[PDB]
Amino acid sequence: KAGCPDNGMSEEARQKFLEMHNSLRSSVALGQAKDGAGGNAPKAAKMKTMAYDCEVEKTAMNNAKQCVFKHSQPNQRKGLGENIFMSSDSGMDKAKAAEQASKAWFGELAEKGVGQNLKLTGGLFSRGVGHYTQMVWQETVKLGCYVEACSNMCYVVCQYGPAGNMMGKDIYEKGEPCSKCENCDKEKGLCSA
Ligand SMILES: [Co+2]
Image (cartoon, rainbow, N blue to C red; front, side, top):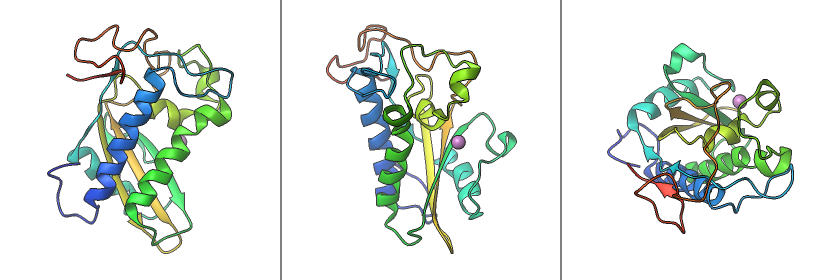
């Protein structure tokens, strides 16, 4: 979602990825997101707005173009986190793929649960909610994704800068929406720079 190269990724898909990420981060920040562990995820005091980044898309593309479903190694995406997703519908619309990937990742919260302790402990890290926690990582403010049509799958990779899912760190700071940032609408809960 914007000024990126004509590289096979659709603008519609870029826009959908960013829109979904910010919308879902907002829902969490406002205390509106159901948590499988009980109640809703806690409100966030300074959930940051994401922007789309063409350079992050470039390293996401390096993974997706391989048409093998797997996480890239850290040095193949220096300083970035990563979520991956696949569908058997190889030729599906890329915007539709963006929506499905974003929902599947976010769904870990409702389905597996996270709870009110947002410190990324070894326990939490091992419960398989790492796609969700990366989507709502407070300090992650750059998003870049690529969707590749492969022989047997539609393969989706998003990368995230700076990387989230840092062990021992909080996913986000708890508090009333906007309570710890200036450029923020109390009814949205997202902080801009
Ligand atoms: Co993963």
